[PDB]
Amino acid sequence: GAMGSHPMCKEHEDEKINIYCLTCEVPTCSMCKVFGIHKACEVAPLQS
Amino acid sequence: GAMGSHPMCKEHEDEKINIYCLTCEVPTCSMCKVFGIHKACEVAPLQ
Ligand SMILES: [Zn+2]
Ligand SMILES: [Zn+2]
Ligand SMILES: [Zn+2]
Ligand SMILES: [Zn+2]
């Protein structure tokens, strides 16, 4: 969604929260999955 | 012409081009690595 409405990652300030970590049960960002703390996790797109 | 903006992924329109596929040697987006055609590749942040 639009900037100003879409929550941004605390770790990656320029990345929208755009995925869901199924392993951790938290929404998070794709950079956290590629390079960060959710690298080992099962994740899914939030969508849209 | 306009001032700068951040290039966005063709496949993932809401995603910034924010990584570099070291394998394919091309800039791409993190969603292409997570779920897309670069899932198999080694990548790094443009940062
Ligand atoms: Zn993140
Ligand atoms: Zn996780
Ligand atoms: Zn992409
Ligand atoms: Zn690649």
Image: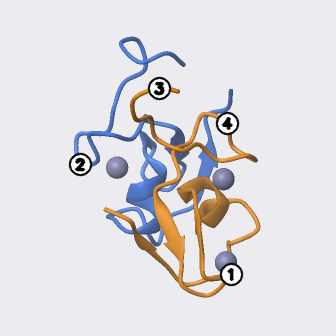
Chain colours: A blue, B orange
Q: Secondary structure at mark 3?
A: loop
Q: Are marks 1 and 2 in contact (CB under 8 Å)?
A: no
Q: Residue at x 53, y 27 (%)?
A: B1
Give the mark nearest the N terminus, 3 or 4: 3
Contact check, label 2 and label 4, Cβ < 8 Å: no
Q: Ligand 3: does it lie within 8 Å of the C-beta at label 4?
A: no
Residue B20 position, x and y percent, is 51, 71
Q: Is mark 1 within 8 Å of ligand 4?
A: yes
Query: In this figure, which residue is indicated by the disc labeled 4?
Result: B13
Quadrant of residue B23 within the rendered picture: bottom right
Residue plotted at (60% across, 34% down): B14
Q: Quadrant of residue A32?
A: bottom left
Please name the residue that numbered disc 1 is placed on: B40
Q: Secondary structure under badge 1?
A: loop
- Name, please, the residue furthest toward the front: B1
Other residues around mark 3 within 10 Å, as few (<14) / some (14–19) / many (≥20): few
Query: Looking at numbered disc 3 in the image, what kind of residue is underneath it?
Result: Ala
Which residue lies under the disc numbered 3? B2
Distance CA(mark 1)–CA(mark 3): 36 Å
Residue denoted by label 2: A11
Q: Nearer the viewer, mark 2 or mark 4?
A: 4
Judged from the image, the quadrant occupied by ligand 4 is bottom right
* Label 4 CA crowd tier, 10 Å (few <14, some 14–19, many 20+): few
Q: Are marks 3 and 4 in contact (CB under 8 Å)?
A: no
> Could you tell me if the residues under marks 4 and 1 are in contact, i.e. CB atoms within 8 Å?
no
Q: Are dots 4 and 1 on a single chain?
A: yes
Q: Residue at x 23, y 40 (%)?
A: A10
Q: Secondary structure at mark 2?
A: loop
